[PDB]
Image 1 (cartoon, rainbow, N blue to C red):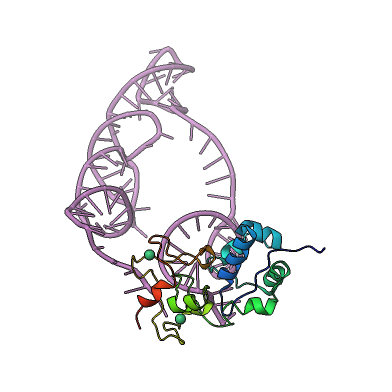
Image 2: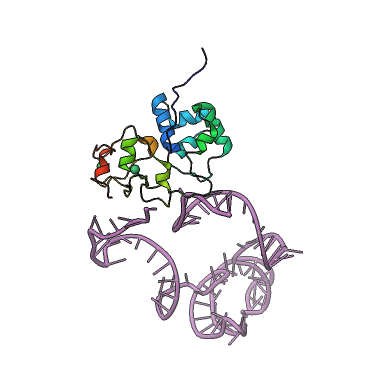
Length: 161
RNA sequence: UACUGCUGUAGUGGCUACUGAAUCACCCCCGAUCAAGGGGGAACCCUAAAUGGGUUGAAAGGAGAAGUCAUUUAAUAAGGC
Ligand SMILES: [Zn+2]
Ligand SMILES: [Zn+2]
C-alpha cells in the first residue's frame, strides 16, 4: 500500500477556487488545513476568493500539485492565462453550463466575458430570482443559491438569451 | 462586469472670514509687536534707612537640501509590469 488521498480529477475550464473546494469537500479538509498540508500556509484560503494580489507562483502551484496530484500545467490551466484580467467579484455563473457540468468556469470571471459562447446567454452575476450574489466557487457545496435554495441548473431558464 | 434609492444638517468632520480670554515669569497700567519700551507698586536682603542699590524658575543647540525606511490613515486596484 502507498500513501493516498481522495483524489479528484479536474474538470474542463473549472476554476482553481472551485477545484480546490471540491478537493476539500471530498477530503473533509479546511483552507488552513489544505494550506498546511501543501506547505504554503493560508495562501490557499486566499485563492478561494480569487485574491491573486501576488499571482499564484510556480512554486505555490507545484506545492499544490504535490498534494492534489494534478499536473502543474493543468493547475495553471484553471488560472487566467498570463495577461488576462479577471474580476474577483462578483462571482458569475451560467446556468446551462452548470447543468451540462456542475462546476464554476474560470472563463466566467474574465473581465471581457459577458456571453456564454456555447449557449448565447448573458451569464448571471446574481441569483435571478432573489438577487442574492453567489458565494465563492470553493464554497459551492452543491448547486443552489444559499438564500433561496434554487438549483443552479434551474437558473438556466431565467437567465436572458 | 458598475451599482444605486429608502437621507434629516440628522450625526460627525474639514476649510475660510470675522470675532471671546489669557498676550505672562514677583504684581499693575499705557505701548509697540518686520518693533519699544516707558512708568507705577509689593515682598525680601544689603542698607539704621535713601524707586539709594540689588533678588522675587531653569536648561540645549548643526543647519539646509534630496532621497529612503517604518507606522498609521485615505483612495484606488483585483496584480503590477
Ligand atoms: Zn453556458
Ligand atoms: Zn437565490
